[PDB]
Image (cartoon, rainbow, N blue to C red; front, side, top):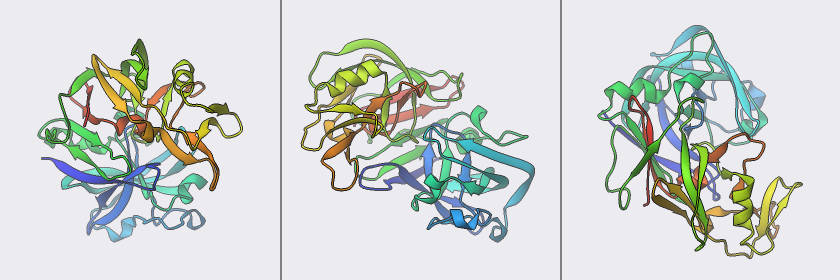
Length: 330
């Protein structure tokens, strides 16, 4: 089997991407944030505290003939931005782009933090990291990809995120028309439950490539590119007027600037992030200070290849017995 679904930016900055997901019978379609940095599929629901729902579409398990309460199971999760949610669990039929999993754990939110309430466009998350990170207790649950894997033509999914444009998540096959050149594969460590890999270095603009190992995660659920302070300083030093602002919470730059590209290494191959991808717009409405899309990972504890990086590539998440990651230009 295979599946294919379009993923769409939630706003004009590509802050996140939503993908429609069919849950239950008859189908209830919710727009979920596919997140390769977490492993819970959770949704706004009829059980979510009323004051914490503001425009999202909810899953109502009582209206699904295939929903079953997973007795005794609860979940609770926190993300890198400090947001959180928690609740109980149902099993139900979940389909993505034509690919159907029965008995998928659908984690129903009783509580969500303000950041979720305030974002009307995201109805929940669909985790695509390794199932060892799933927060369901007392019986950990498998991700949608893990449940689908054995039925797929090939045990893979691919992320093809657009810049200010829709893109595609595919399951079970590699669309060879979707990228240019070849896909370069690189080793993955699953020790932390993430799609963790080591980039071979970087370049700033037309500058020379610096060969240096950068361990980080491929995380579709993080907006920006978070890299070591040395790397980030080297980037922003090429932008007149750019500075790290403690009050704003990262590097900012004059909105009048033209940003240089940023290249990262995948083995001997190179992925180029165009400078425009690194512009996240005014820090506040009407400001001439713009927020940078490359930021320091210092004090996150890990480097994160988020959407800024991933959207410059066609990315293969290879879930073979020994997982690997593949990157191609496009």
